[PDB]
Length: 48
Length: 48
Image (tube, rainbow over all chains, first blue to last red; front, side, top):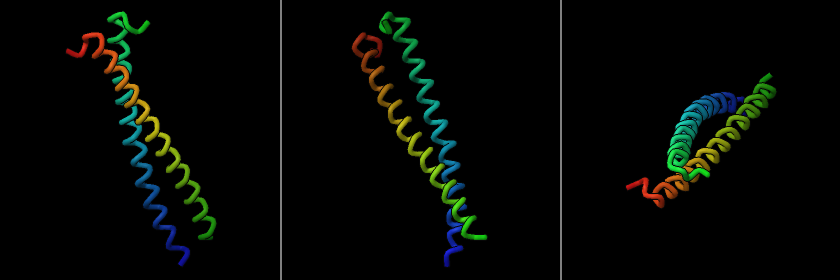
């Protein structure tokens, strides 16, 4: 009964650990874009 | 025994699920930041 949770949680945790690495890269990619756009605004006089 | 192993797996689980929620919120806020920057660029003639 109860012990069957062990494999379920082990496998879910592996999936979640992988998902964290894919979201870290996606978030980082968006940060690089924000920096690029900020610079473009700054070079054009529009970032204060 | 197995009860304690399960408790530990659940704690890891919630730690991972909480980090995913956070990165989903962070990613979304960055996409909104990208939208706002793009709209500024568009208004100042920098996006064609």
